[PDB]
Image (cartoon, rainbow, N blue to C red; front, side, top):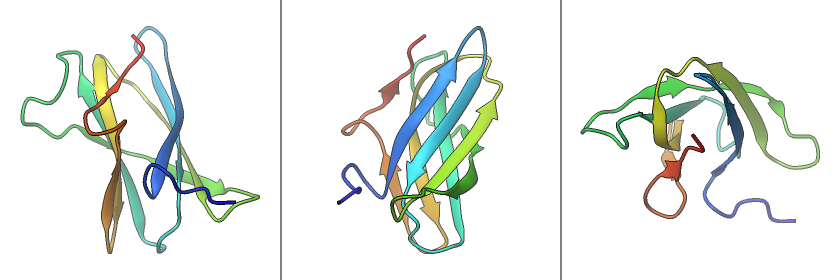
Amino acid sequence: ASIPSSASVQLDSYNYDGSTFSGKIYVKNIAYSKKVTVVYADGSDNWNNNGNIIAASFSGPISGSNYEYWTFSASVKGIKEFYIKYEVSGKTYYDNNNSANYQVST
């Protein structure tokens, strides 16, 4: 089957409660030196020409497909919007709704 659809990467899911972020990601292995970077926007709603990034960490290869599987927990004090970036030591892409921002269910 063909996994890629949105981009090289697609957001799996994340959780929230009080002030807590816990997120994991579903992305293809292009090369090896990859660095997955969250950009999740503050409780001001969207970036004021800023770049609030928090690096995600790989958990392991996704058994059953040619993809990798990323996880991390974050202490966020105020979030509202976001999009996750796929930054590679060769390329860069974006997983972002359509062309705007993911609204965080707060």
